[PDB]
Amino acid sequence: MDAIKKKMQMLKLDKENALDRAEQAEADKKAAEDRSKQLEDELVSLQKKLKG
Amino acid sequence: LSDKLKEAETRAEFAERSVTKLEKSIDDLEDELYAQKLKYKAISEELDHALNDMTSI
Image 1 (cartoon, each protein chain N blue to C red):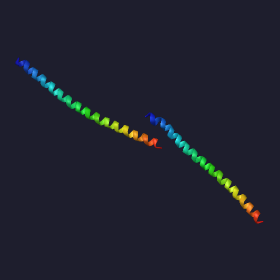
Image 2: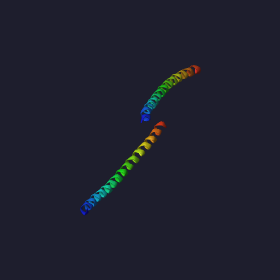
Image 3: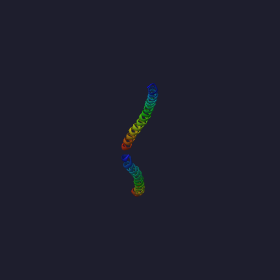
C-alpha cells in the first residue's frame, strides 16, 4: 500500500515530465522553423544578388 | 434409580443433539471463512501484479 502511495508521486512526475518535454520540443521546433525561414529569405536575397 | 436413569438419558440425548448442531455450525463458519480468505489472497496477488505494472513504466 505504501509502495503504491509513494510511487504514485513518481507516476505524476513522469506524466508532468512527458508534458513538459513535449512543450519544450514544440517550442524548439518553432524556433528552428523561424530561423530556417529567415535563413531561406537571406539565401534567396543573396541568390538574386549573385545573379545580378 | 429408574427415574434417575431416564432423566440422565434425556439430558445425554440433549447434549448429543447440541454437539451435532455445533459441529454443523463450525463446519459452515469454516467454509465461509475459507472462501473469504481465498478472496483476500487473490486480492493481494492481483495488487502485487498491479504494483509491478506501475513499476514497469
